[PDB]
Image (cartoon, coloured by chain):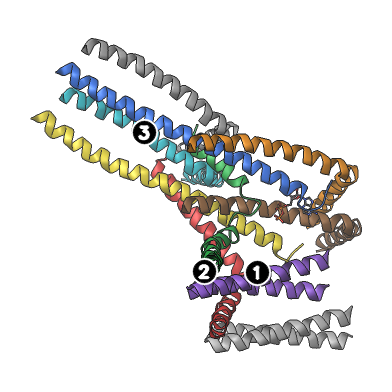
Chain colours: A green, B red, C blue, D yellow, F cyan, G orange, H brown, I purple
Amino acid sequence: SSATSAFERMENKVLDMEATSQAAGELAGFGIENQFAQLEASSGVEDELAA
Amino acid sequence: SSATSAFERMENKVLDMEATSQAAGELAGFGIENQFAQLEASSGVEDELAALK
Amino acid sequence: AQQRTMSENLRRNLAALEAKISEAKTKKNMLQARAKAAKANAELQQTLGGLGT
Amino acid sequence: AQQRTMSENLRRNLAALEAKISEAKTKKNMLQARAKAAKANAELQQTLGGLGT
Amino acid sequence: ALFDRLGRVVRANLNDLVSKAEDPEKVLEQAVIDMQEDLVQLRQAVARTIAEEK
Amino acid sequence: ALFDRLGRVVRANLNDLVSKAEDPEKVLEQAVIDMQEDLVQLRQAVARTIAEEK
Amino acid sequence: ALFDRLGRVVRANLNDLVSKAEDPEKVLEQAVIDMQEDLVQLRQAVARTIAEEK
Amino acid sequence: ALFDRLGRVVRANLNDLVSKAEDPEKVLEQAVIDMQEDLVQLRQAVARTIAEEK
Amino acid sequence: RTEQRLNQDTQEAKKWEDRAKLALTNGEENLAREALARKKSLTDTAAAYQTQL
Amino acid sequence: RTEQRLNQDTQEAKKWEDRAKLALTNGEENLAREALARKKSLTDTAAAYQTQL
Ligand SMILES: Nc1ncnc2c1ncn2[C@@H]1O[C@H](COP(=O)(O)OP(=O)(O)O)[C@@H](O)[C@H]1O
């Protein structure tokens, strides 16, 4: 009956293809921040000059 | 016969299983810290050098 | 006055119930999606895993 | 007056028992988790172990 | 004590057998279907207390 | 007294056997079930008491 | 040890018999067919989380 | 002790026979299967633990 | 296959090096340290594969 | 095969020995001792193999 039990059953199988997440976890955190930052900044000054 | 007594019994059994596993590893060859200590010290000096340049 | 305050409280119990059911529907569906995701991952881990037929 | 005094005593004891049961319930889950983790660690140690055939 | 412990062991074993047999996804789904029905039943009953109030 | 000693050995063996037969995963869970089962009935009594007070 | 080794030898032999019987080209093909189906099932389930989000 | 010696000979022969019966190609592979089978179950435990932590 | 594995690990090591440095520029030494540990980890694995090749 | 086993043991002995340098720098005295003791046992093993060879 438990919704929680339903979640667990699924939750394990999710586990087997690696889910400790030392990659996805690590990656995303500093990735999204750093990339967009340096990108738009440098790019933007250069763009405006030519416009 | 009571639930609480049964629980205390299962709880001790579980703690004993955690303890068995821990001891079993040490006897087997437990390194961990060794590797960990070197990787900690390496990342440190490397970041320092990285930052320096 | 007795009927009005009784009905108001009963109405509140009804709203609470509905809110909880809404919550359960939202939860149900994300778990179904996650379950299908787990299954899909498993199939790729099978086909594109190690050796065998 | 007698009813009010006595029905309040019963509430103190229900409240204590509720704290108690929920304690066991939460510990039940984490203990099962700890136990499965430990059980598994022991299994891996045996499989990975080179001692014995 | 022997049988008292046997009883506890037995109930747990029985509950586990139930848990094993128990598809949790149908339980949760089936549950939503019944909860929705109950919600509707409550709405009708409430409708009657509103009629009476009026 | 040898009869009593024999009984003690028999019971000790059987008590050890049923202790061995415990499955914490099943049993710990079952124990909690018993706790809840029991509470529900206490709540029913507190339910009556409260109603009587009113 | 004798039976412990026998067990390992036996499982390997059994797996090999399976590997032998196993057409790998149908496995891979069959797999793509199921993976495509699963992809579709995920798309529907995702569609529901999108509906809920909206 | 002659009984124990006889047993040792019997077991040694049978151990040599099952060692001979090993097929590295099958067996080495089977051993890896066992490793994976075992890991999967560890991962399930780590799965629960992580969920409980959350 | 071994040749392929070696190159793949080498490439990932370069991406993690880049990431450590980008993160370091943006700030946070501890974050850079974490990235470096992974960088080293992949570098070490790559070395092993090189020798194997 | 004798040569192959022994050669290997000599490489493993260096890995313990060069690990001991890092442990000593850190101030991991017990880990450093165990590493040296491991190096001794491998040295003893290697000697036994040479004779055998
Ligand atoms: N030789 C093999 N190598 C890898 N996997 C295999 C092999 N033979 C069969 N398999 C199947 O592939 C799965 C590999 O286990 P899995 O834990 O997914 O791998 P990993 O531990 O690398 O993630 C097993 O469940 C097994 O049924």
**Chain letter of disc 3 in the image:** F
Tell me which residue sits at (27%, 22%) in the image. C10
Q: Are marks 1 and 3 on the same chain?
A: no
Q: Tag 1, which secondary structure?
A: helix
Query: Label 1 vs label 3: CA separation?
Result: 60 Å
Q: Tag 3, which secondary structure?
A: helix
Q: Nearer the viewer, residue D1 or C31?
A: C31
Tell me which residue sits at (57%, 75%) in the image. I21
Quadrant in the rendering for residue A9 = top right
Q: Which mark is residue F38?
A: 3
Quadrant in the rendering for residue I42 = bottom right
Q: Which mark is residue D38?
A: none
Query: Label 1 vs label 2: CA separation?
Result: 26 Å
Q: Where is mark 2, residue-wise?
A: A45
Query: Label 2 vs label 3: CA separation?
Result: 72 Å
Q: Where is mark 1, residue-wise?
A: I15
**Callout 1: 10 Å neighbours few (<14), some, many (20+)?**
few
The three-letter code of the residue at mark 2 reads: Val
Residue D20 in the image: x percent, y percent?
A: 33, 45
